[PDB]
Each structure stands twice: as C-alpha cells, then as structure tokens.
Amino acid sequence: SSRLFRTQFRMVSPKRISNPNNTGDSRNCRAGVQINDSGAALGYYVSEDGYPGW
Amino acid sequence: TTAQLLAANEQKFKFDPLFLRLFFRESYPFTTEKVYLSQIPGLVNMALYVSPIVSGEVIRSRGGSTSEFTPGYVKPKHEVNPQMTLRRLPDEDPQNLADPAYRRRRIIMQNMRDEELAIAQVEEMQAVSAVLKGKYTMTGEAFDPVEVDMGRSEENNITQSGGTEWSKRDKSTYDPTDDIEAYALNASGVVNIIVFDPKGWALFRSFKAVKEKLDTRRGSNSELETAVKDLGKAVSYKGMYGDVAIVVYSGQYVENGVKKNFLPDNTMVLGNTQARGLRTYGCIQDADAQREGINASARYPKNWVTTGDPAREFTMIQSAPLMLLADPDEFVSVQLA
Image 1 (tube, chains in turn green, purple):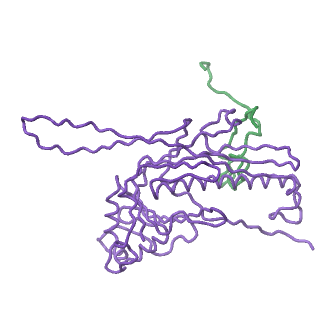
Image 2 (tube, helix red, strand yellow; image 1 turned 120 degrees about the horizontal axis):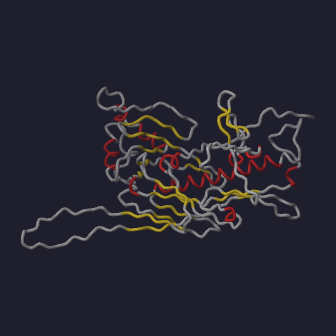
Image 3 (tube, chains in turn red, purple; image 1 turned 60 degrees about the vertical axis):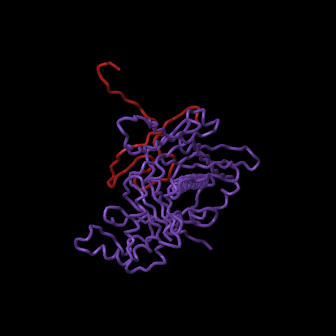
C-alpha cells in the first residue's frame, strides 16, 4: 500500500497457537508458546486454517 | 487390593541420523515425474608433437552423459477403535484415572510418533546405503522394485583381500597411515572426515605406531582420545588425526523384531564434510491431498473414519522420499577386514 502508515494489525483466534505437527509438549515449548530458561516467551507457532480442510 | 503408579519408563534405541545430517543438506522438492543428473568427463589429452607441415588431427569436443531417476513411495498407517479404549493404559495409575475419551488422545499421539520414527528410519537407511556403495535398490512386497544407480567407479569401494588386511598383519611395526593415504588417493576431491564402525575403530587404534603419533613433540599435530569417551550415544566426535576429523558412528534400525546396526561390521568410509548431497522428495499421490494444493511435500498427514460396525479412526503419514548423490565417486569405502 501507498497510504501514510504501513502498520497493520490482525486479531488471531486462540486456536491457531499449538505445537508444530501436533508433537508432544516439552519443557520449553508448551501449547505452541516457546519458553526460554526464564519465564519469558520468545516466539509463537501460528498455524494455517483451511476452511474446506479437515 | 489397590495400587499406585510411581513411575513408568520408556525403552528406545540409539538412533541418530548422522549420515543424513552431515552429507545430505539443502533439500529439493520437485513436482516432476523424473529427475536428471549430469556429469561431464573433463579429461583432456596432452598435446602430441606435430610437425609444422602436417597440420591435422582435430580433437573432438568433450561431451557428458545423463541419468534418469524416479522416487519411491512410503505410507505407514495406524488405527484406534473403542474396543481397546475402555480397559486401561499401562502408563496410568489405578488411582485418579482418566476418561474413556482422554485415552483416545494418547494412543493417537503414540501412533503419530511411531509413524514419524518409521519414516525417519527409512530416510536414514536410504541415505546410508548410497554412501557405502554407489547404488541402492528400493523394494518391498507390494511395491514393484526400482533401483537407483549412481555411477561410481570400480576403483572405489576398496575391499581388502588375502593380501593387505589389517587383522592378519601384526600390530607392532605396522603403520596404517600408509594405507589411509593409498586408499584416499582414489578419491576425486579433498577428503576431510572419516566414519568408523566401532569395531573398525577398535581395530585401528590398536596399532602401536598410531599410539606413537600422539605423544610425539613435533612429529605431528594430531590429538585424539584413545580412552573411553561415549558409551551410550550413537555418535562420538573424537579428535582429529593430522588434518582429518575422525567419527565413530553406531546407529540402530529395526527390520522385523530384531535390532540391526547401520554400518556393517567395521567398515571405514572416507569423505568430505562438504560433500555435495541432494535430498529430493517426490510427489505425494492422494486425490484428497491434491485438493489443498499440497504436492511434492514431505510427510502429509491425514485421518478418517470408516463408519464400520466396530468403528475405527485411522491415522496416516506418507512421504515418497529419494536420496541422491551429485558426485558419486567422491567418497571412498573400505571393507577393512
């Protein structure tokens, strides 16, 4: 876009945050939120939703 | 009589895809029936002396050759039915317990993990079988057999014979460095790493000259570990030997109920840590897969319900993997018997 501001937002449904390929939960990556040695959260695993898809 | 489940272990084998990791990187997915690999001879005769009169004998321009390959197909599947969900699980305590529907999301996870592990084992076996010998054959009971054959020179795959075998000749006054040089002379390109089956490593380090090459002040720069370093792990990155790196690989794959080792009983493999290797994935063939758009991808999962009399909700993974080596004669395989 050639508007004044290039910032855009997107509200993500909570169901799209989960482990890759439905692997088991780990010590550092629980329910799609990867956690370092401390309690901080580093990055999230946003899935892809296909409405005709199962 | 009551009970409590305090602990419940899991049993596995030493599985680690070293050969896939080191030598096979930069995967290429391809939406094509068959792929090509081309080699150009690059061999120029020295110019024969010609009088300034005759002025002839044109020399042909060099031309290469091509090879055609096709990928296989692999699909393991699992199942789960309400008949086996009711009773109990071997990793659940008699107290508390879980619901007859939560036990349905443990068997599913176990199944998916087993499918992924089987696919990984297939990929590792395909990767290893190409390194040891130039060609490997892909076959099964329902799959029509196809063979992938990279062109590897006969000078490689050096197998020891009645003469020049390390086992027979004495461990004092013999140096194997002479041999590791003559064997490496056949390789095309610099070699940088050696892979030892554990018995081969045990046979190699027994030589007294090798133990001399460690504690010499200026005779070399190699540092090794002739003590015990790794006892349970599948790979053990030991020290360098002059310039080359030494690795001992002992991996396990199971065909039928038994366990088997990947490297066959004390082989030694030369090679380069930057060897050009290809990881190609074929086209998955499911008419429900081709709907999404997914094609020439790795590990397409799916599941469905059969609506049969005892029900059942299956689970499935399918990959269609292929392993290729762009330069086949760059490695050197030694029987070392």
